[PDB]
Image (cartoon, rainbow, N blue to C red; front, side, top):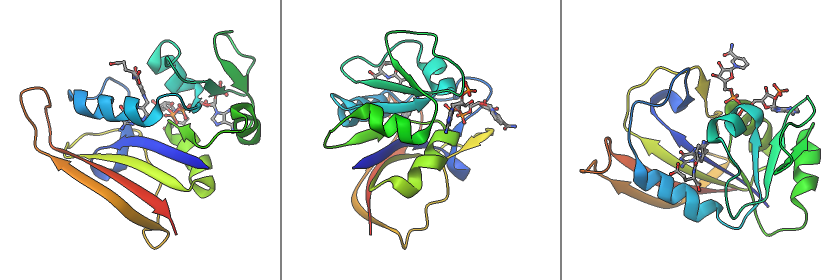
Length: 159
Ligand SMILES: NC(=O)c1ccc[n+]([C@@H]2O[C@H](COP(=O)([O-])OP(=O)(O)OC[C@H]3O[C@@H](n4cnc5c(N)ncnc54)[C@H](OP(=O)(O)O)[C@@H]3O)[C@@H](O)[C@H]2O)c1
Ligand SMILES: Nc1nc(=O)c2nc(CNc3ccc(C(=O)N[C@@H](CCC(=O)O)C(=O)O)cc3)cnc2[nH]1
């Protein structure tokens, strides 16, 4: 079982040149609880963004180039990424855009945070046709003193 997890603003924006213009510590907590003790596959740019291995997770990094950090596992293909996760109940694909695009057709679950933020970015979560996906969980949150925007956690499972 392969799952994708992603935080989407408007227009499914997930990434931009600079740090996202928001502070969403609840979404970070959601990402951690949904990824903890699972293998995480990410692309090299997301690996760079994160800065260090996600603790408590087997970290698998996709790059066409040789790896540059022996703390994590580097693979050169989608299939090698999956294989490098081993035999687990659930692989979490944590982005970014090129990685999500390649893993979405493989995935059985999506964990999406829909953030009510108007941002320009160069990177978008893929179109998922909702005839393919059933929303099994939905939880909306207003912005508050810790969270700059309203956001909604959703889990979809593939039909
Ligand atoms: N014109 C564009 O918009 C464009 C096009 C490409 C990239 N970018 C820039 O990259 C940033 C974020 O991109 P992202 O979120 O898409 O990054 P991402 O998915 O986190 O990382 C992408 C990197 O992962 C590796 N990768 C992904 N799939 C692979 C595969 N099947 N086999 C081998 N390696 C694989 C490649 O690493 P290596 O590079 O080490 O091979 C690729 O460059 C953006 O700020 C964006 O501007 C932009
Ligand atoms: N829902 C969701 N929110 C996200 O921010 C998110 N981010 C990514 C990719 N980028 C990142 C960047 C940093 C960390 C990160 O450092 N998380 C730490 C908590 C430490 C912190 O507070 O920064 C973790 O342990 O998961 C994770 C993913 C992928 N899916 C997402 N999914």
